[PDB]
C-alpha cells in the first residue's frame, strides 16, 4: 500500500513542506492566513491565496487499476467584520493537476477560470462559499462539492458562527466512491453533513496536488478572513489488486 500523510497541529513560517501562493502567509502565531489582512487589522478585498502540500499525491494507478481512499481534517475560521457591503467569497479544499498555479480569484475561489463545466479542469473541491454568485444557490454560506466546475453538483447551507473555529472532516471511500464531508462548530454544537458519489478516476489525474485556497471579493470592503489553524491529510493506495 502506497501511503502518504502529514499533520500540522500548528503552522511554522519557513516550513518547506508547504508551498504558499498569492497572498497566503503563515503568521508568527502559527496561523495560516489564506487571504491578506491589512495593517489596520481589517481583511483586504481582491485577495487570493493558496497553500499546497509540497509533494504530489498518488491518487489512482492505471497499471493496477486501484484507487486511493483518503481523509483530510482542518480547522478554520471566517470572520466577517461587516454586514455591508456583502462579504465574499470563501475558501476551498481542492485536488487538481500537479504544478498548478492560482486560477481566477473572487467567486472562482482561486481554482477555476469561469463558471463552465469543463473536464479539462481535472479538479475536485469542497468549498465553504460565503457569497451568492449567479451560479450559486441563494443561500450563503453553503458547503459545496465541486467537480470540474464552480457550479456545485451538491450544496448544503450552513450558519456561520462569525469568527469562531470550525472543524472539518472530509473522507473519500474508494470502494463506494462516496465523498463525505462534515462541518462542526464546537462553539454552538452545530453539525452539518453532505455527501455525494464521485469517481475520482474519471475526474482527477493519477498524481495530484492537494491544497487549500481562499479569496475575497472584487468590490471594496467585500472581504472576510480565511484563517486555517491546523491541517492533516492521509491517503492509502492499494499497490495491487489480485
Ligand atoms: Ca460564490
Ligand atoms: Mn457555491
Image (cartoon, grey):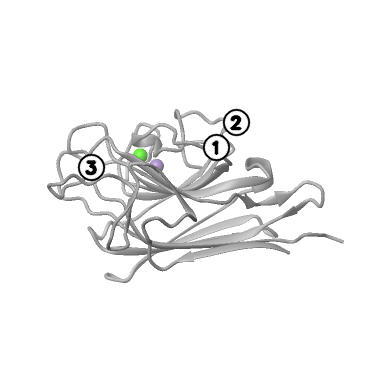
Of the image marks 2 and 1, the number of the one nearer the N terminus = 2
Which of the image's four quarters has the N terminus?
bottom right
Residue 129 x %, y %: 36, 46
Asked if the residue under mark 1 is in contact with the one under mark 3, i.e. CB atoms within 8 Å, the reply is no
Residue 159, placed above or below residue 117: below
Q: Residues within 10 Å of mark 3 (few under 14, many from 20)?
A: many
As drawn, the label of residue 148 is 1
Q: Secondary structure at mark 2?
A: helix
Q: Quadrant of residue 240?
A: bottom right
Q: Nearer the viewer, residue 83 or 77?
A: 77
Q: Decide if residue 130 is on the left or right side of residue 135.
A: left
Quadrant for ligand 1? top left
Q: Are circles 2 and 1 on residues that touch, CB within 8 Å?
A: yes
Residue 223 has which mark?
A: 3
Q: Mark 2 — residue?
A: 120
The image quadrant that residue 10 belongs to is bottom left
In which quadrant of the rendered view does residue 2 lie?
bottom right
Neighbours of disc 2 within 10 Å: few (<14), some (14-19), many (20+): few
Ranked by sequence position, the earlier of labels 3 and 1 is 1
Which quadrant, please, contains the C terminus? bottom right
Frontmost residue, 27 versus 177: 27
Q: Spatial distance from mark 3 to mark 1, Cα to Cα?
A: 25 Å
For label 1, count other residues whose C-alpha is less than 10 Å away and answer few (under 14), some (14-19) or many (20+).
many
Q: Tell whether 68 sits left or right of 50.
A: right
Which residue lies at the image location 53% right of the left edge and 31% below the top edge?
117
Q: Measuring from the top left, give residue 73's x and y in whole percent.
A: 47, 63
> Which is closer to the viewer, label 3 or label 1?
3
Amino acid at each position: 500500500v502506497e501511503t502518504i500523510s502529514f499533520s500540522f497541529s500548528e503552522f511554522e513560517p519557513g516550513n518547506d513542506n508547504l508551498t504558499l501562493q498569492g497572498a497566503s502567509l503563515i503568521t508568527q502565531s502559527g496561523v495560516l492566513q489564506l487571504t491578506k489582512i491589512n495593517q489596520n487589522g481589517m481583511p483586504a478585498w481582491d485577495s487570493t491565496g493558496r497553500t499546497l502540500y509540497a509533494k504530489p499525491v498518488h491518487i489512482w494507478d492505471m497499471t493496477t487499476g486501484t484507487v486511493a481512499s483518503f481523509e483530510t481534517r482542518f480547522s478554520f475560521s471566517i470572520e466577517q467584520p461587516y454586514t455591508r457591503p456583502l462579504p465574499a467569497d470563501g475558501l476551498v479544499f481542492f485536488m487538481g493537476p500537479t504544478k498548478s498555479k492560482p486560477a481566477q480569484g473572487g467567486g472562482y475561489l482561486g481554482i477555476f477560470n469561469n463558471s463552465k463545466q469543463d473536464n479539462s479542469y481535472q479538479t475536485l473541491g469542497v468549498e465553504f462559499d460565503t457569497f451568492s454568485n449567479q451560479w450559486d444557490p441563494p443561500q450563503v454560506p453553503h458547503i459545496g462539492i465541486d467537480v470540474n466546475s464552480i457550479r456545485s453538483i451538491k450544496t448544503q447551507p450552513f450558519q456561520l458562527d462569525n469568527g469562531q473555529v470550525a472543524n472539518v472532516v472530509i473522507k473519500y471511500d474508494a470502494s463506494s466512491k462516496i465523498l463525505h464531508a462534515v462541518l462542526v462548530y464546537p462553539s454552538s454544537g452545530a453539525i452539518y453533513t453532505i455527501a455525494e458519489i464521485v469517481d475520482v478516476k474519471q475526474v482527477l489525474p493519477e498524481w495530484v496536488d492537494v491544497g487549500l485556497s481562499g479569496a475575497t471579493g472584487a468590490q471594496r470592503d467585500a472581504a472576510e478572513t480565511h484563517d486555517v489553524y491546523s491541517w492533516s491529510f492521509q491517503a492509502s493506495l492499494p499497490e495491487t489488486n489480485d
